[PDB]
Image (cartoon, rainbow over all chains, first blue to last red; front, side):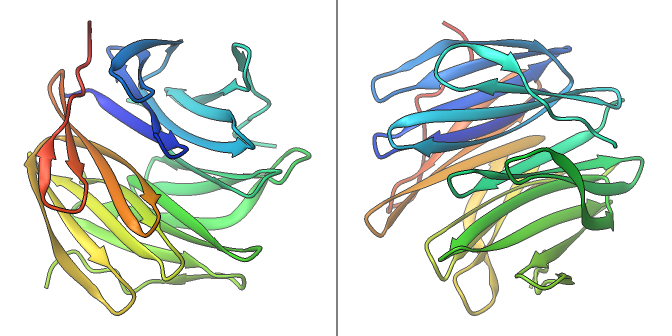
Length: 90
Length: 90
Length: 90
């Protein structure tokens, strides 16, 4: 078929993050104004969406990774990706 | 295969909305700072994207739901989801 | 199957752009406050994501178009779509 991407950006430089789901794995490419590099994000999933917001100059990111009917939320809040509270039902 | 999601967020809390297309139906999970709950959005579609913007503190949301080659726009503007003017051609 | 869309918006009017991948081709519909029209964007791809940001009142847009395992970045910066520096690896 084809890979699936999600993108987000922030600030005025801007920083950009592109998430790619490929063969069950989601990886991350980053731009902070100079060039593209690989980011810390590495999680399983066949589909991905993303949103982010600033608190002052600190970025917060939520990546929604889906495999089958299970969507897991992954959070960046300044110190590592942690799994989020998101659930699909209830 | 797998479900497909789209996500958007606003404000500083933030509020978050995650839309999930699953088996022809798009449903909505919401976060306003405390926990996740099911939102009012319920429309047919196999694919979804979303964008939103603030006017002061009031949120406006546009959800693009696609089935086959027909994309329908759905609008939140403070008082219920209504169908939008979006058309694909002409 | 079904077409795939990505959406972005900016400003307070707002302007909206909806990108649709359909049968290998990504096209663009635009809203600047009056009605929907077809935009300049026309590129190959089976999947698309998008992000955008303002610098003052000038919009900058990045559209990520994927075919197979090749994601090409397309840039709008006020004067035509140009191909971006994005690469997936290295």
